[PDB]
Structure formats: structure tokens, C-alpha cells
Image (cartoon, rainbow, N blue to C red; front, side, top):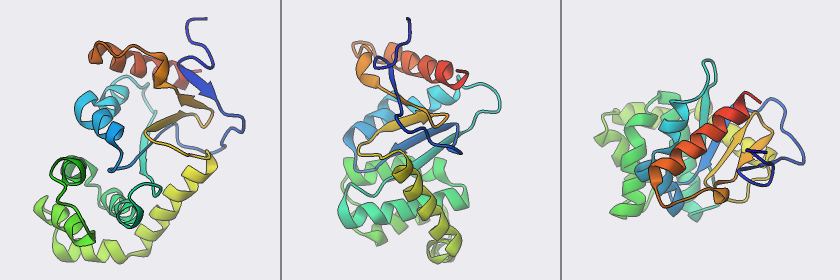
Length: 188
């Protein structure tokens, strides 16, 4: 009665088997995603409260930004393969939404090089089949949950957070409420 289906979370009509424990979907073109990540720091706070042995997976989506949107999903695949997510998240969000200097795949590449990834290192990964399967994996997960909007977060392949049922006057309280709900749903 404190946490209710339809309130702070909804239950999937068709639960996804084999889905990562905590799955977050976002797009660098998504305004609210920018807030979530850069201002609210939702992911960090959720991570800081998850039980031991529970891992967080973050995927990018194709349905926003058209051409550049698909480029970013591939670039995110590159970030995951190389293990440089924590180096490129901020400059990618800022590049797309703050300075609006990211206008083509080349501009995305510049961000990685500026972050310290070698040109030849990036170019090889970008064309690699390991990156291709990483892109397919991201697309498949979005298909499995019939994703139609971001940001979104799913727990154990059964529940989807519903931030609408929470107070936004104090950001810190909203974040903690969100984090606590994920912890609850993960051990449920």
C-alpha cells in the first residue's frame, strides 16, 4: 500500500525474460534525459542504492534525432565496447543540447578524440562487428519492452518506473524517492 502498481511503477503486461536487472533507456536528443543525467544525476543515485550484485545497463535509442540518432546509438555502442562511457556522456549531452555543435558523425568522433581515445582506436571499433552486435542488442531490448518513450527504466524485466507519481519541488527528495523505489522493486 506504500508502493502501488499504477502509482510509482507499472507492471509489464508481457514480462521480459533474461532482461538486465536494471535497464535504463535514453537519447542524447531527449531534453528530460539531459535533466535526468546532468542535473538530477538519477543513474548515480540509483547505483549508490542498489543491492550488491545488481548491475545497471544503459542503452541509447534510435527513435529521436533521425540520422544523427542512429549515429549516436552506434557511438554509444563504441563507448560501451571501449569502456569509456564515463568519459563521453557529458560532452555528448552538452554537444547535442548545450552547444549544439554535434551535427554529424564526424562531430561525434571529435568528442571521443578530445576525450583521449585514439583516432585509429575509434575508427576500428566504429566499424567492428563487436560494435554491430552491441547496436543490435540495444535495439532488441527496446523491442522487447515495446519502448515508445525516454527516459525509461525497467527492473527485473517486469516493472517500469513511473516518475509521474512523485513530487518535484525538491530535486534531492524526488531523486531519493526514485532511487528507493528501484531498490524496492529490485528486491521484490
